[PDB]
Length: 49
Length: 142
Length: 97
Length: 49
Ligand SMILES: *[C@@H]1O[C@H](CO)[C@@H](O[C@@H]2O[C@H](CO)[C@@H](O)[C@H](O)[C@H]2NC(C)=O)[C@H](O)[C@H]1NC(C)=O
Ligand SMILES: *[C@@H]1O[C@H](CO)[C@@H](O[C@@H]2O[C@H](CO)[C@@H](O)[C@H](O)[C@H]2NC(C)=O)[C@H](O)[C@H]1NC(C)=O
Ligand SMILES: *[C@@H]1O[C@H](CO)[C@@H](O)[C@H](O)[C@H]1NC(C)=O
Ligand SMILES: *[C@@H]1O[C@H](CO)[C@@H](O)[C@H](O)[C@H]1NC(C)=O
Ligand SMILES: *[C@@H]1O[C@H](CO)[C@@H](O)[C@H](O)[C@H]1NC(C)=O
Image (cartoon, rainbow over all chains, first blue to last red):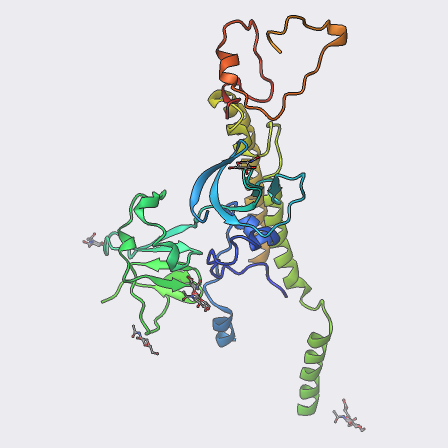
């Protein structure tokens, strides 16, 4: 299963200049549509499991 | 370039940071466009270079509180923000939030959810009190 | 009984290491989440009967009073595009719950 | 265009290219001489911008 963003820290580093064009997540983000991270990380889910 | 500005190219008004583009506009083009039908690159009509337009930095802001009955002290989370973009949130570049005492720093923390200010990071783990995201919580304690 | 268990767990690795589509129930959730945000970004490109889909093309070209008749079309259509997304997400969240 | 001595008959209406020039439309719109001045996808107030 391959995810389309996970809320992990879009730094203004990558999404500025080049990746603004070729990534749907920047077109979403620039229009006020943001993804929030889950409270339990995939490491915390694996510790419970 | 590299500053947030009110641009206008040939009547094409907008707001954003202008940046050096690597794009390859053919001689008949003047603007590049997005999936959203908004422009995102433009050719300067005086020196024929291509400028990437990007919007000025923004995010959600969220306020963390033990409640008014416990204290009037709060911590602020800037959602999806690296800490270096809060020194960019200086009063010289007037932001939508007029308040700013948080920018005094010293207790700035970076989480995968965003930049957290006014909360003290500690190595001790506890049961989650107020959930911040990406494995982090906050609580009001001695 | 142990050799049959160890062989049966072996076939879980072989199946998951082989076929592309076994997690189709989880990839469908990611695909529905992504499709709804990509559809919501596409509804920004629509005019809804305004002279342009872009507020800067209305606010550069029209005066303060002829602009509002165009801006309210874009507000009306977008506001329905958010109420559609949030209704789809509230219905879809009950499937996931 | 506007002060040319002879206008065309409507059955053979004239068409002039306006090109590589600055157009101060405030001078055209400020003149009270025009009995009608109607703009159909733009406001006459904005033509200078
Ligand atoms: C926050 O932004 C800073 C840059 O302003 C990032 O620091 C860089 O991180 C990379 C990868 O670890 C290093 O190669 C660089 O040398 C770092 N630069 C500096 C000036 O220290 C930092 O990683 C960002 N953090 C997050 C979570 O976004
Ligand atoms: C019960 O079934 C198992 C297999 O499910 C049988 O075990 C196999 O027995 C053959 C010889 O008869 C061996 O070649 C296989 O290697 C065995 N497999 C395993 C997993 O050990 C078992 O013999 C059957 N028992 C009875 C009483 O019929
Ligand atoms: C703008 O001015 C410079 C000279 O300062 C000139 O080189 C350039 O060609 C001009 N732009 C256009 C569109 O001619
Ligand atoms: C907080 O609430 C309790 C009642 O649950 C009350 O007794 C107490 O005086 C309150 N304190 C403040 C500062 O509001
Ligand atoms: C947390 O532990 C690290 C060492 O693992 C140490 O460098 C750091 O100063 C500690 N922070 C606190 C608040 O105790």
